[PDB]
Image (cartoon, rainbow, N blue to C red):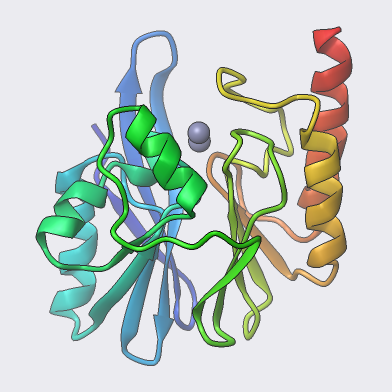
Length: 218
Ligand SMILES: [Zn+2]
Ligand SMILES: [Zn+2]
């Protein structure tokens, strides 16, 4: 099983990539980010496991950084698997109240901090959490970095195919995807969960795949 990967994307922005093996899929990988605000560090999604989340934390803590908060883009374990351990560490965890509501239903540990609004600033003018509408899941949120013009779209951004439809809203995804496009028309980079990095075109490609996957389902 490949090691938790950490790669500097640019100043103050790192992509963490963790790995899971699941029968009927082989070895799956998952991208999140760590975002620095000066010497404050923020986790955008957690690794699948407590153990990899710890490694991720330690890596930055040992380099001097203070883990100030974590935000999970949706309720599925590939974003939320580390929440429990981080809670036991008194490292502050966030999720929208819908994500938290869905985590509870799933029998999962909830984030300690939440918010009810479409938009929420985790750091004043530096980290914005935004809910486009239902897509991959009812609750999926994106994370925007205004200074850098980087959008982490989580599993909502699916330019090459929609992936797991298990909890999806095919009816709503096209609308949500358009809302996303209209909000962040000047994105320079778009980091997704299971696709390589790209520019703002990825948001259009998602709208397109949403519209396709929808038609297919009828
Ligand atoms: Zn998911
Ligand atoms: Zn995913």
